[PDB]
Image 1 (cartoon, rainbow, N blue to C red):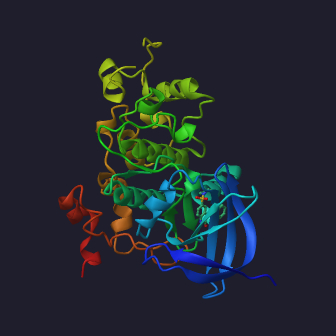
Image 2 (image 1 turned 135 degrees about the vertical axis):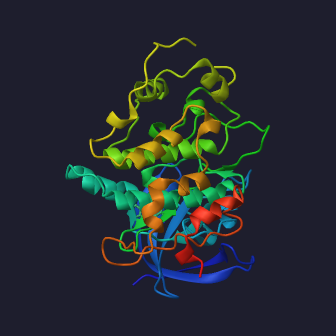
Length: 348
Ligand SMILES: CCN(CC)S(=O)(=O)c1ccc2c(c1)/C(=C1/Nc3ccccc3/C1=N\O)C(=O)N2
């Protein structure tokens, strides 16, 4: 039975390369970036995922740079990295070895969707709350993810622990230094990007989070456009034509549209949708980027009260994961929020 030994650098520790041995290799994902494998660490039998990407020798890998910095319970941890050869000989591949997690928010929601059901709202709150924590943490470093969607939210369904993954589009955003407008997956892409903004902020991640939340409530994407222009048309059918001031706030440059009225929020969603879910969604899916809640404010929204109840359990009987162990860094955008975020029973 085949074992592979490589010399790998620890993700967060000091740059002393070390021998790492793994076995039980299988393909579990792929994309334009390259390929993702599952493997088992001989060391501790622990399962990991190995993401293998092509390395341009002109420039450093920004994915690697960003992932080395990250240490959070709701973010897939970079354990090691190493270099190898691969398919296109005389080329160098970067291998990222990450926490392995067996499900995605997308897969779980599709199980329900295929059965013509929607996910119980307790799971919607657990997932969305963990998404907003991981966004609060990355945004506190100025890092924007730029590809928030259900497929990038890994899940352990026994524990309900969620971890953000795929930092392939992520970037440190610097005020006055321009960024590409054509990013994010289309269904989740903020309107200021559709309008060609290059000066956008971390708030585009919040718009994407709002789209994930509405998909969970609806059982299908809320804005399924076939192109960028048709993406705006989908957005408009629900939100109405953006006003002049809204366009200005989105892109101080970028027309006359068919004047179309906002669809009432309550009838976008199924009859019995909790009002608090709808009110949250409306404060995420705003045209004016500055009007959207921050990640930390989203966590403190009433929609998530049930998670702060001392007697709350997962449906399967087990205790909820870590939800209240906020750090100084996490709270930094708005320290007084801690009084809400950390309930009395979680301080002790
Ligand atoms: C989805 C995000 N990626 C692109 C495939 S990724 O950055 O390469 C990436 C990175 C670390 C990762 C993963 C994916 C990952 C994944 N576990 C899974 C289990 C079932 C189906 C898909 C995945 C999956 N991925 O589809 C995992 O356990 N650690």
